Length: 123
Ligand SMILES: [Mg+2]
Image 1 (tube, rainbow, N blue to C red):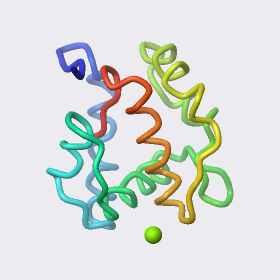
Image 2 (image 1 turned 90 degrees about the horizontal axis):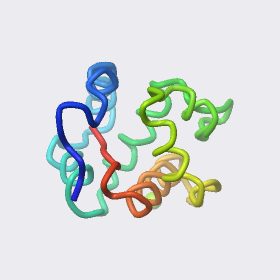
Image 3 (image 1 turned 90 degrees about the vertical axis):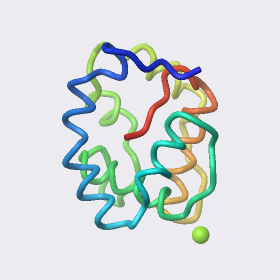
């Protein structure tokens, strides 16, 4: 079951993600419910959600010159409290597959959620 309490997900990270959520939901058209369901419930297929995921990586400045996720930039952008969790969650998710940047972004989130459903979250 996903860990959801006063300390996790890190409140400061959730707060920082709010304006990125607004920008990305406005650009991609994903619904609030699709995001919450992927975060807390089952992995599901939603093309706008995949693009929302890609958009968050771009808005968080954790992508390379072609828009692909740079995993070191991503790790560095996270609070230290989740560095360990992130490393294990991603150690078998190093090389995304997918045609589009949205497909690859979804590949990452699915791989992370499959690896550690307790700590995975999406906002
Ligand atoms: Mg497609």
